[PDB]
Length: 282
Ligand SMILES: C[C@@H]1CCN(C(=O)CC#N)C[C@@H]1N(C)c1ncnc2[nH]ccc12
Image (cartoon, rainbow, N blue to C red; front, side, top):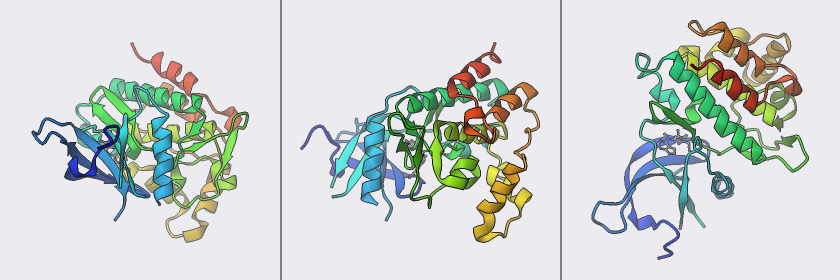
């Protein structure tokens, strides 16, 4: 009965879609007319951290892009739910293993371009994503993907180059650049690094045995507990990186390597990546 919001009683629950840090996402049909003509929507709620969800809502409200999941609205309870468009094929992490024979290198490069476009937009808006990994890239169809979660996303202040994180507890460390691990500083160039790791996942079709975590654990050892990040940083300082996936051509690997320069100022920009991938298409 605020017509500008979604009524909780009409978000007809269908099934779970996924879980993240603070939240879970569920598929609902929003059916206020009660005649089953309403649309299916994805609904993010706090897990069975209110301030955190509200910050994520403010970010997604402020984003509108072809390769960013579409904000639809809010449902208010105190509590709040974030309402988004539903993207039926789910994340790249679940979609790619099911579609190896359907998705070729050409299609993978088109996804790389779409990811880089959403990311260049995000950066232009002075946000750092902080969780760019295949599990957060949603597939609308065979031909299009969108960045689909913003739970760790932060604003960089005008004229500043990084955001300093005070709370690193949710951090995907095997997707993180050295400055994020060593100083909790997050630059747009730190999201470039994460994108290189995401690209690696995309090229290995998100095989679990080739995941950045599984691969780095093999390099540094799996039982270091709280010394894990320390060993990761040591490895990176030594210049080691994830290898070229087999079936990844050298020209693509070179783009990936440009995301992995140790120093953030030495890394490629997302605009340069967009153009670099497009030169490999047709
Ligand atoms: C890949 C999407 C982003 C990460 N997901 C989370 O649940 C994060 C949390 N908490 C799953 C979600 N997912 C499977 C979706 N599946 C279908 N439509 C969706 N719209 C928005 C998300 C979404």
